[PDB]
Length: 271
Ligand SMILES: CCC(=O)N[C@H]1CCN(c2ncc(C(N)=O)c(N)n2)C1
Image 1 (cartoon, rainbow, N blue to C red):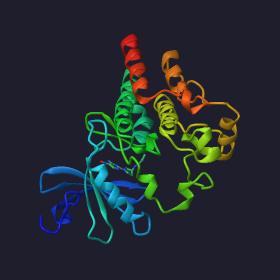
Image 2 (cartoon, protein in one colour):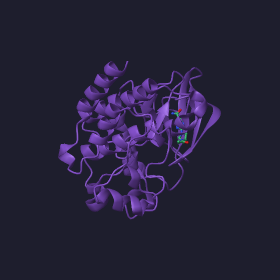
Image 3 (tube, rainbow, N blue to C red):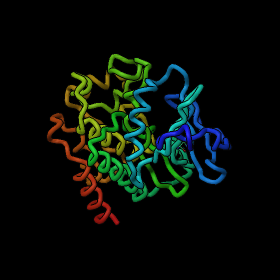
């Protein structure tokens, strides 16, 4: 209460239960808030984040709410490392989930995963909010198998310069359109391109895009107009959708609303 804004959680209300893994900002734990509510607790490693800028942005993120978006519940700011408190996603990151062959996915389940993400992205686009680093590694899966988009916008606060421009060794080259790699031109349409690569990741059961290429080679391939090709599990109609995200001209790429319509049509035709 006293001492806390609407965006601030009291860390004393947290009970820590299990480790969930380690990501861009360090370790993530599963816990409860006020004894009952499941939460994930991202513990932000010292020196990793532009914390004041992130905290100001968290106030904006508190107002993003969609069933296919991992919900931000608040932040613990008064602290050693600061915490980000979010919705708990018991089945972990999508990339790893796709790679577990025991699931024996049907293609209708793969298309549903694409739809889940596309709905979240259509919501973000309706708010004029870019993800800026969409990829399977940044999607999460709940106990019901629903995929949700996470960490939206957070790349803006990463202090490790290896991540933050193409000149960096950890930049998401394989998820970037030509205008990002050539000129650093980010837009809705760079999220669209990344979404198409994400559909490729889903239909490829978690393969690395351009698996036989380095990042440098990938950039040369794409900037010469060449592309990923059709995963074996994708129908022609699904392939057409992902491929439409990769138009050399950003303005000729679809919106998320259009992509959603196309996905629904294929779900109806393939059902
Ligand atoms: C493929 C990527 C990966 O290994 N990610 C690690 C670091 C972030 N992460 C995570 N983050 C949040 C939640 C959550 N909200 O429940 C969760 N289950 N797991 C697991």
